[PDB]
Each structure stands twice: as C-alpha cells, then as structure tokens.
Amino acid sequence: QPRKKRPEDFKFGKILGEGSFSTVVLARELATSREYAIKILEKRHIIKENKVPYVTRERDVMSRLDHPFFVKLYFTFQDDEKLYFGLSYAKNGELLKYIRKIGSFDETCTRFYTAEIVSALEYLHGKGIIHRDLKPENILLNEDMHIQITDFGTAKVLSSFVGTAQYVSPELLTEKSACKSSDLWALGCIIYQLVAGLPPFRAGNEYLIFQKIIKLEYDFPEKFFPKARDLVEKLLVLDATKRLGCEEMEGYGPLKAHPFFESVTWENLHQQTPPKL
Ligand SMILES: O=c1nc[nH]c2ccccc12
C-alpha cells in the first residue's frame, strides 16, 4: 500500500458540512489533482464525550462498503490533534436540496431514486449493517446524479441511539430497539417526502412528532401516486415484522416486485441515466 497520506499532501478548500464531532472539508490532493471530501475529527473532543466507539464503528463500517450507491473511504491518517477520513466527494450535494428546489418529484423521478435507495439498502442489509439515520440530508448526489448514501457514525452492525425525529421508527420510541426494518420505516418516510414534498410526521416539537409516529397519525395528499401510496402504506406499519422488505416478509424480493417498481431494471441502476429533475 502507498505510504500514509498527510495534511501537507492536500490543499484544503471550503467546508462541506459541520457536525458536533466532525467537519467535512473539500480537499484537492496535490500529486493527483483529485478532490476528496475529508472528514476531520478532533481526538480530544471525541474522547471527552465518549465517542470512540462511534468513530471506530463509522470507520469500520465504511471500510466494508464497496458499492456505487455508498460513500467510499479511500484513506485515513491522523496528526496530533485530528483524525482525517478521505471520502468520495458528492459534487451535487443533498437529495434534500433537490426536494426543496423543485418542490416534489414526478412519478418517474420518484420511482428511479426510490429504486436506487432500495437497491442500496438491499446491499447494506445483506451485510448485516443497519444505517439507523437514513434521511434526505444524508443521501447525497454525485456529479452523475446517482445517489451516494453517507453518515455511518450511528450505524449498527448486527451480530441505544436515536436518529432524526421525523424519520424515527415506532419501535425505537417504545423499546429502544432497532433492526433492518427501522431503515425500511425511514424509506417509507422518504418516499412519502419525495412525492408530497414534505415528511409524513410533522409537528411543533419532537414530543409531538413522536406522539404522531406511535399513533401512525399522518395522511396522504389527494395528488399522491396511487401505487406509491400503496407502497408507503406497506412500509409505515407499526409492527416492524410486517414491513415490506423485512425478513419476516421474506426480504427484498417482494419489495422489489411491488407494482410501483413495475418498469424498473434492478440489475444495473448505476449504469442507467437518471431522469432529469
Ligand atoms: O461529499 C461528501 N461525501 C461524503 N460524506 C459527506 C458528508 C458531508 C458532506 C459531504 C460529504
């Protein structure tokens, strides 16, 4: 393998994202002129707040991913104060940006992007990995407008944590337990948001959102594609063992065979040209 990279190998540019424990900065490697999104984490702050297990798990999960619809981890290094993770740069930003820009997706764009997300989840879940915080903010778009799912700090590897309120599955609120089917619940919220323009469970504060989620209190706009509504109803199901895609429903085959996806070719989505948004 190549000798470890270091900060001096790059010219750092603009900040791409900021979290409580990390900052992602666009960087151009001098020897190659390649651009990477470098996630930078301060060792002191991680240790102080007991985040070592999360940072360790994020790195370890990313190392295992080798699929076009996921962030790729190219390299890591550290200096005295900071860890550096070299990630694929998703030039077009967040799916959420496009939702806002255009309001809501037509049926062809909903179908295509939903199919990429389902195909990515099939790969992720086949590895026994659960994302636990899936949402349009961490579904990025590459230069070619294919998805690149990111943000694995909170993932779980199948042999505690609660993600973003609007996408939280009822079982987390009633058990503190997660599973693959929790990602599928989030998928149901995302589809709904692509079609309606907004997430299904909304309210003034988290407490009230949580109330709506555990009561399955949401509804569909009249202009909701009927087949997409049927799919969303089969995903937003309080009983986690009855969600389309979960093991107790015999997995991804029946999900991928849903009528909403009739015209989808599953085998080579990454090779297909995405519908203009
Ligand atoms: O461009 C990115 N690629 C991977 N992860 C990210 C996280 C935040 C902002 C950008 C990125």
Image (cartoon, rainbow, N blue to C red):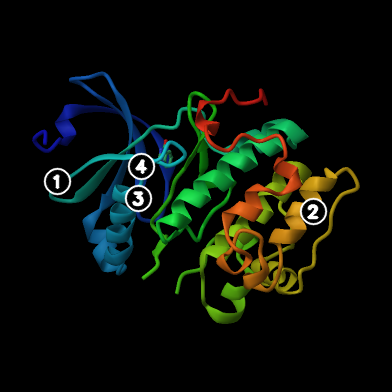
State the quadrant of the N terminus. Answer: top left
Label 3: which residue? Answer: 22
Residue that label 1 marks: 79
User: Could you classify mark 2 by the number of other residues whose Cα lies within 10 Å: few (under 14), some (14-19), or many (20 or more)?
Assistant: some
Question: Which of disc 3 and disc 1 is earlier in sequence?
Answer: 3
Residue 238 vs 164, above or below: the answer is below
Q: How far apart are marks 1 and 4 (CA)?
A: 27 Å
x, y percentage for residue 96?
61, 40
What element does badge 3 sit on?
loop
Q: What element carries label 4?
A: loop
The disc placed on residue 66 is: 4
Amino acid at circle 4: Asp
Mark 3 or mark 2: which comes first in sequence? 3
Q: Is residue 201 visible?
A: no
For the residue marked with disc 1, what is the amino acid? Answer: Asp
Amino acid at pointer 2: Asp
Residue of label 2: 230
Location of residue 215 with respect to 201 vertically, above or below: below
Q: Is residue 56 left or right of residue 23?
A: left
Horizontal side, residue 30 vs residue 138: left or right: left
